[PDB]
Image (cartoon, coloured by chain):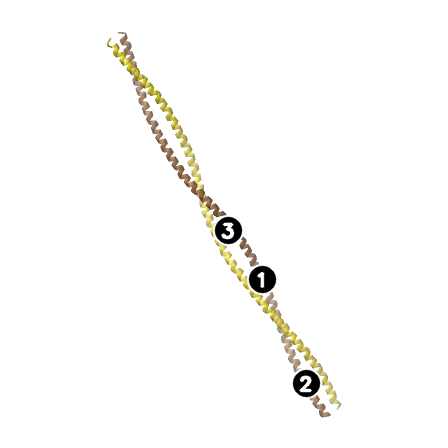
Chain colours: A yellow, B brown
């Protein structure tokens, strides 16, 4: 019967070790599940962080599109302004070239007029002298005619 | 005391059986939990790299926005200068074009006054030729009267 007593002892032994292996495994499993849970929690948070940044990216892309359209407007308005400016400068430039030619034409006409006035004064003076000459000659003629008449009666 | 021993060996083998099954149950669950953790860790690693990429794209856009702004002010600046120049240029054009009109009028006023003066001159000139003719006539008439006076004094 020493057999039974030895087998009892042998089983008590093995069970002892098996109970320890179970306790060790339960503990290891418990932690392992905690590790997986915390890790899955981290992935979840990262996913939320990525949604947040992706949304911000979208907001900035939308702002860039607005900037892009306003930038085109500015380019257009600058062109339209440039086109009117060139046109205004050109018109001014043309007229100012005309103003110079006209001012010179006036200066010459004003000189021509002044000289014409001098021409008139000069001829008016000669006319004065000629009238006086005709007047003296008519007086002479009158007196000569009367002297001939007087003589003719003698 | 042998029946008692046999039942003990029976119960010990029973607990042993149940224990081996628990060890096998737990080892399988442990493996699965480890693999689950490994998978999730791999996923977190991937998400972190994706997060890094998107965050960088964001910073790049922020940089581009600041450049859009500074350029916006640049545009406003040029539009102001151009608007002022256009205004000064139109004033200049209008004044010059109106000056052309006034000067052309002055020219008409000078040309007509000049025409008139030359008319007045031509006239006095003609009257002068008449008087000059008169002088000739009187000189000849006086000459012959003088001859007659002398002729009469010598009769």
Q: Is residue B73 left or right of residue A137?
A: right
Counting residues from the N terminus, which is met first, the one under dot 2 or under dot 3? 2
Q: Which residue is mark 3?
A: B76
Mark 2, Cα crowd under 10 Å, few <14 / some 14-19 / many 20+, is some
Mark 1, Cα crowd under 10 Å, few <14 / some 14-19 / many 20+, is some
Mark 3 touches mark 1? (CB < 8 Å): no
Q: Are marks 2 and 1 on the same chain?
A: yes
Residue situated furthest left in the rendering = A153
Mark 3, Cα crowd under 10 Å, few <14 / some 14-19 / many 20+, is few
Q: Residue at x 50, y 58 (%)?
A: A66
- The quadrant of the image that shows the N terminus of chain A is bottom right
Chain containing mark 1: B
The percent position of residue A61, horizontal first and vertical second, equals: 53, 60
Q: Are marks 3 and 1 on the same chain?
A: yes
Q: Residue at x 59, y 64 (%)?
A: B51
Marks 3, 1: nearer the viewer: 3
Helix, strand or loop at label 1? It is: helix
Residue A29 falls in image quadrant: bottom right
Mark 2 touches mark 3? (CB < 8 Å): no
Counting residues from the N terminus, which is met first, the one under dot 2 or under dot 1? 2
Helix, strand or loop at label 2? It is: helix
Residue situated furthest top in the rendering = B155
Q: Is residue A74 above or below residue A15?
A: above
Q: Residue at x 41, y 34 (%)?
A: A106
Q: Which residue is mark 1?
A: B55
Label 2 to label 3: alpha-carbon separation: 90 Å
Label 2 to label 1: alpha-carbon separation: 59 Å
Q: Is residue A71 above or below residue A124?
A: below
Chain containing mark 2: B
Let me know if residue A30 appears in the view. Answer: yes
Q: Which residue is mark 2?
A: B15
């Amino acid at each position: 019967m020493k057999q039974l007593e030895d087998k009892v002892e042998e089983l008590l032994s093995k069970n002892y070790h098996l109970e320890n292996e179970v306790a060790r495994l339960k503990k290891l499993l418990e932690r392992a599940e905690e590790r997986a849970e915390l890790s899955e929690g981290k992935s979840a948070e990262l996913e939320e962080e990525l949604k947040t940044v992706t949304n911000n990216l979208k907001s900035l892309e939308a702002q860039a599109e607005k900037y892009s359209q306003k930038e085109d407007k500015y380019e257009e308005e600058i062109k339209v302004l440039s086109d009117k400016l060139k046109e205004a400068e050109t018109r001014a430039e043309f007229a100012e070239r005309s103003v110079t030619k006209l001012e010179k034409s006036i200066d010459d006409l004003e000189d021509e007029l002044y000289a014409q006035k001098l021409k008139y004064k000069a001829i008016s003076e000669e006319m004065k002298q000629l009238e006086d000459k005709v007047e003296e000659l008519l007086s002479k003629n009158y007196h000569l005619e009367n002297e001939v008449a007087r003589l003719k009666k003698l």
